[PDB]
Image (cartoon, helix red, strand yellow):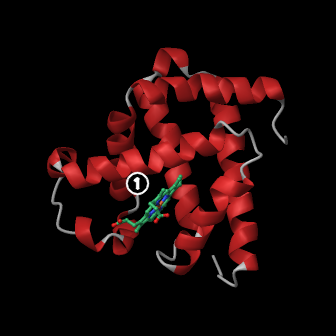
Amino acid sequence: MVLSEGEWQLVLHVWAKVEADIAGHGQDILIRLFKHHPETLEKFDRFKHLKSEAEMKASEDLKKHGVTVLTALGAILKKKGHHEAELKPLAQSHATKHKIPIKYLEFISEAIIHVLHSRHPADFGADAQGAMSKALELFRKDIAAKYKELGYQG
Ligand code: HEM
């Protein structure tokens, strides 16, 4: 839904590349998020001490968390927009426990795109970028709707 089936197939085709190396993509994505938008580490007390990209790359905790994040995102993307049941617990924790504003979800979406462009430049063209961007945008829109239901000013 929202995306055409053909657009979803571009998304899942790019996502298969992510699934070939989930921990590597998750490390890169979190490091890119924290390096570009260091204010986002205010949400991760446990990672505030990491002093360099090298230390971040060597952190097993950070790696495991990237796996957690991308595993959850892959399950969402594979539902192709019919992701109500996967999004419910995620919106709950991120609105009420972690308190993640929508703008931080935009930042991590931009980091996902950047990392895919860095890791797959010869197999991540304009249509694949546009489709992944639409899919992440839909994810954010539906999170925002749940945020509102929950009373959280995202
Ligand atoms: C693609 C977007 C995201 C996905 C799919 C995702 C997914 C997850 C999942 C599955 C968990 C573990 C279970 C839970 O608490 O719900 C988690 C934990 C958490 N997430 Fe997210 N997340 C995303 C974005 C973010 C962003 C952008 C931030 C902060 C800027 C953030 C902050 C946190 C924190 C603080 C935790 C707890 C970490 C800990 O255990 O120490 N999340 N996330």
Residue at image point 58% right, 57% down: 106
Q: Tell me where residue 51 sits by quadrant.
A: bottom left
Residue at image point 70% right, 85% down: 151
Q: In this view, does 148 lie to the left or right of 59?
A: right
Q: How crowded is mark 1: few (under 14 residues within 10 Å), some or many (20 or more)?
A: many
Q: Nearer the viewer, residue 107 or 16?
A: 16
Rendered position, 8 above or below 125: below
Q: Which residue is labeled 1 in the image?
A: 33
Q: Locate residue 128, reporting x and y percent.
A: 65, 26
Q: Is residue 116 left or right of residue 47?
A: right
Task: Quarter of the image for the C terminus: give it.
Answer: bottom right
Q: Three-letter amino acid code at disc 1? A: Leu
Q: Is residue 41 left or right of residue 52?
A: right
Residue at image point 27% right, 53% down: 62
Rendered position, 130 above or below 16: below
Rendered position, 2 above or below 90: above
Q: Tell me where residue 35 sits by quadrant.
A: bottom left
Tell which residue pokes out farthest to the front in this image: 85
Q: Locate residue 13, reporting x and y percent.
A: 61, 22
Residue at image point 15% right, 45% down: 58
Whether the residue carrying mark 1 lies under 8 Å from ligand 1 is answered with yes
Local secondary structure at mark 1: helix
Q: Locate residue 15, reporting x and y percent.
A: 55, 29
Q: Which of 53 and 4 is in front in this view?
A: 4
Q: Locate residue 143, reporting x and y percent.
A: 68, 63
